[PDB]
Image (cartoon, rainbow, N blue to C red):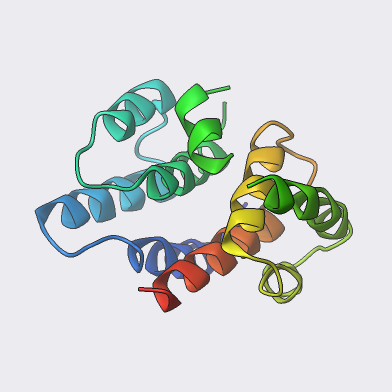
Amino acid sequence: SSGMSLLTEVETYVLSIIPSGPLKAEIAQKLEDVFAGKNTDLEALMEWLKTRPILSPLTKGILGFVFTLTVPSRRRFVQNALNDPNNMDRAVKLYKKLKREITFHGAKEVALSYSTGALASCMGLIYNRMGTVTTEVAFGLVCATCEQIADSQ
């Protein structure tokens, strides 16, 4: 049900944290294919991600979250990338707040007042609790995380 308006917005946030190069172009193509519904093979996408050079653990965690979110129907490296104790403790409070949000921007507004670590940890929480927030809310969190990372670059 996620329209292309939202999905293209997400593409730009996710790509903003990736260093320029042929790898980024490959990720862009894969993102486009997954978002369009032209690739539903999550296992291969996860193996591809896991074996990629250059990308930071957190970048891989974000990508893994985004793929899992957009493919119809757990992965240890994703959780490990997203999982800091103080960041984890704020993640639960944020998660509870996000459960009550509906929209992309409602979620983004709430999330942006949290640290990158807390946002990553909250993504970890949601990764193991798919369907407990709206897709827009999950994307709002991703984009808030990407915004903070890009602004620290």
